[PDB]
Amino acid sequence: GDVADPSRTKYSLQYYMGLAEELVRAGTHILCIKDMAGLLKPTACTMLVSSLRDRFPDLPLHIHTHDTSGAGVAAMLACAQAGADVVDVAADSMSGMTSQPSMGALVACTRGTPLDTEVPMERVFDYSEYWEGARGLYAAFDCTATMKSGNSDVYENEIPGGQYTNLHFQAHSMGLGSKFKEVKKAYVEANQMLGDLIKVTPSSKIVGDLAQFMVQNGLSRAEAEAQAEELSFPRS
Amino acid sequence: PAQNRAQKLLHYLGHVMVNGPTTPIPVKASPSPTDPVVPAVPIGPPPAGFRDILLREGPEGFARAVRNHPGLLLMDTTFRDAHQSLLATRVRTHDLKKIAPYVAHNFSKLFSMENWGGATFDVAMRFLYECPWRRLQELRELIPNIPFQMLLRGANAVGYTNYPDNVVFKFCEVAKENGMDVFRVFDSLNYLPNMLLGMEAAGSAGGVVEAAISYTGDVADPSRTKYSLQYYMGLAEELVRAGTHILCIKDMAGLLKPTACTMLVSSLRDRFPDLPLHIHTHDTSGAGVAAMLACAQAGADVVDVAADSMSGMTSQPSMGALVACTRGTPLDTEVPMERVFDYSEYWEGARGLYAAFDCTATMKSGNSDVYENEIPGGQYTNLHFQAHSMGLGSKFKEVKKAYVEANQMLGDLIKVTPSSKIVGDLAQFMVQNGLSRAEAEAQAEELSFPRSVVEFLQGYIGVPHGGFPEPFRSKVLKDLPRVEGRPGASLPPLDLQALEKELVDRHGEEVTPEDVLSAAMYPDVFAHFKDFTATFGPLDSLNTRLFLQGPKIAEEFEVELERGKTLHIKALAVSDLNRAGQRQVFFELNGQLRSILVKDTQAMKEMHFHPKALKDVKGQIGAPMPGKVIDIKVVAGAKVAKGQPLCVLSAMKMETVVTSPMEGTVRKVHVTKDMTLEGDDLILEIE
Ligand SMILES: O=CCCCC[C@@H]1SC[C@@H]2NC(=O)N[C@@H]21
Ligand SMILES: O=CCCCC[C@@H]1SC[C@@H]2NC(=O)N[C@@H]21
């Protein structure tokens, strides 16, 4: 969802704060916000992380996102400014797109501020160069075969990074590769039909299997809900 | 004269089937077999945009309307800057026209669209064999409501050398007449006298003058004193006093960190409250979206963006990312996200047609080493392709290190075209010869530097901030002539009427003012472009796959020449080689058999290279690069002095003068005019 969007009432700021209170009462050492799709906009980051920090001044706050939207670096900088203690990053050659924000970008942007990571940039470059060579050994599995950059349609479809790559490979294996735009639209419809549940493994796969099933059978949401007693749905 | 357009197109298609691509392909990738899907466009004229204000109220009215706009304005680089960086400016007029009506309707609120200047002018003629002026005119008809923006070099227009002032003025006049609206005037060294001429030329044409300060260094780093905040503020004061309508910060490499953005843009806004501030960056570091958000928060009125599938890496920040991040804030762009997605999907398909030129063949993501090397987006892609062509591809890390050393040796000048190329040529020269900075500076009287480095040190591009590096300049130049002041100011006015008459005598009565200016700026390129289009016809009518790879046997396709004139073409067969060294290509054209005789150089290609220069024999002069012999300045038996010109090589589009390392007598010359040499091939012997 989007805590900065007052029209999205199901996954509101109050929902996140109430769940954080139950997890803190249960004795968590660290509280994590896991944005598995890259949906945290910088404004939503600021609002959520400051509210958590104000409520829990002594608790470590860890923020995880994906750079699927191409805004993940800006989102993590906004979290850090709002009082996150830790952010998830990847080596630069293993960052961006459906991965985490760039380590070198975060280290460079925080340098000489109160948020400095103290990581030497030369060490990040040598680390990235190794991973650039190593990624070349995995060209047969690289998401860049199908997705050349981040995509902002993730704010509409809410498909997690690892599910996007898998759903595309599955759609291609089923002869639906030319219809992958219809599969993404059906993923939104399937999420709503299922009740707009959080989408991460395995729930992200359940929505994916339903979306492929709808596109394969030429079904709209309304037809799939009307015929729900007659249709053989995916096992998941 | 009967028009023969269809036969000329079949001759091009037959040429590509026999000889391969006419455009040099840098990587073994094939264009997509599928054409891009064009999104649906409303029937009617597009909504009124910022161009309607510019046409009604002039440049100052436009600048006031930009400053008074509630929210962040966007400018689209996809039309030029985005591909220049990603696909090396290879994007064709054909693909730009297909999406243009969609842009006009859905992006009517853009500040401007950047679609012409920079490398697009030369590249259109040289490599795409299309007229850049026709591209401007046809796009202006399809997009009547958005201001068109160009990147203009101040005293060089879109060219690579300095021109007489009357050529720069006449270029800006004819560019404005052809529908150019905004002139982003920059200099490669921020050399104010070159910028002032370009501002005066663009303003006198009735264009919107946008004076652009090229950004280098780090204003947030107190150790970097040369390009300090005070340097940028002082140059901004001179450009504002010179009557700029808009002030641009041009970060050509992606060096603006969010803290540096905040500091520079707030200081400019506090100094100039009523002046529009335009910020341009590249996303080379992967921080460009965060940098543009920091500029917008610091009071920038406009930021450069690209379509999402044409953004990131060496391109601009993502349009969809900026639109999404500003939504529901005081900086909202009011652009609907669905329209950005449809625009990106078209460009994702279109980018697939250019896979043969894609920077992702060599660079898989942005790279933060740009904060150390300061290599601009378009120079990074070109420097890598050049290094690979010279057998230095495995040493590209050494080339990047040598680029830093070369920048320092040259004096840490701003690095943008052509100064970014000058540093690149020196860096490749250092790595090729195994030279450190200290060795290259020590041996500066003995070494034959790249022509671009020599011409820079002579002053042919203007004067760098802080002056030229001494004693290094004096050692390289010796007795070579030096240009003091502005290089164009000493050139006699070009007689454009005499040139028009020469072109009419050579090409017939259809010569236009645009043709005269194209010939004035790029004589050899324009001549080659006219001869090529005289042979092969209007290649802009072909889709990009057929232009690059030609048709497959039994492939059928349509070519629209003009509204209501479609050619149905099918490729049928290619014959064996005849006794004249030609193949016969068979087509069906509108249900009829056609055949064309073509020429297969590949079928019959052979050569032999004798020449080698012993590295230990000072009198044996080897070729310093692979290249073609343009001129031979000496004969056997001639006495030669140390530093005397011996031959001229033309390689990588750069005349290199080979000079004598010693005094002596030329014993033997081993080369001829038009001979192709490899590296170290023996040119001549000196005793
Ligand atoms: O091919 C079969 C599945 C292979 C594992 C896919 C993983 S499970 C963790 C993550 N979440 C998903 O929905 N898919 C991936
Ligand atoms: O292959 C020869 C050069 C082709 C044009 C390269 C363009 S000029 C504009 C931009 N700046 C550079 O340094 N290179 C590109």
Image: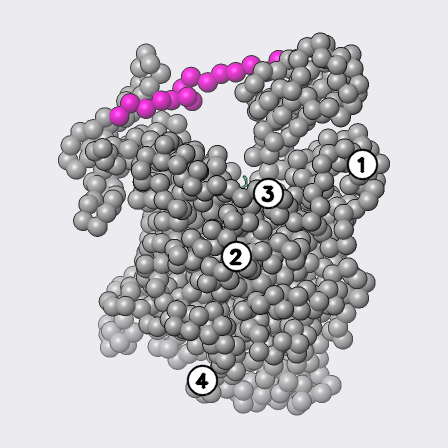
Residue at 57%, 74% (x, y): give it: B275
The three-letter amino acid code for the residue at tag 1 is: Lys
Magenta range is B596-610
Q: Is residue B576 visible?
A: yes
- Gap between marks 4 and 1, in whole Å? 70 Å
| Residue B602 magenta | yes
Task: Identify the residue under disc 2.
Answer: B201
Q: Is residue B469 above or below residue B590?
A: below
Discs 4 and 2 lie in a common subunit: no
Host chain of mark 1: B
> What label sits on residue A115 in the rendered view?
none
The three-letter amino acid code for the residue at tag 4 is: Arg
Discs 1 and 3 lie in a common subunit: yes
Closest to the observer: A54 or B446? B446
Q: Mark 1 or mark 3: name the one nearer the start of the chain.
A: 1
| Disc number lying in front (3 or 2) | 3
Task: Identify the residue under disc 1.
Answer: B475
The three-letter amino acid code for the residue at tag 2 is: Ala
| Residue A110 magenta | no
Q: What element carries label 4?
A: loop
Give the x, y percent position of residue A66: 56, 67
Q: Is residue B492 above or below residue B194?
A: above
Residue at 48%, 37% (x, y): give it: B523
Q: In the picture provided, is B440 more to the left or to the right than B496?
A: right
> What label sits on residue A8 in the rendered view?
4
Closest to the observer: B595 or A152? B595
- Gap between marks 1 and 3, in whole Å? 27 Å
Q: Mark 3 or mark 2: name the one nearer the start of the chain.
A: 2
- Gap between marks 4 and 3, in whole Å? 67 Å
- The secondary structure making up most of the magenta span is loop
* Rendered image quadrant of residue A45: bottom right
Q: Mark 2 or mark 1: name the one nearer the start of the chain.
A: 2
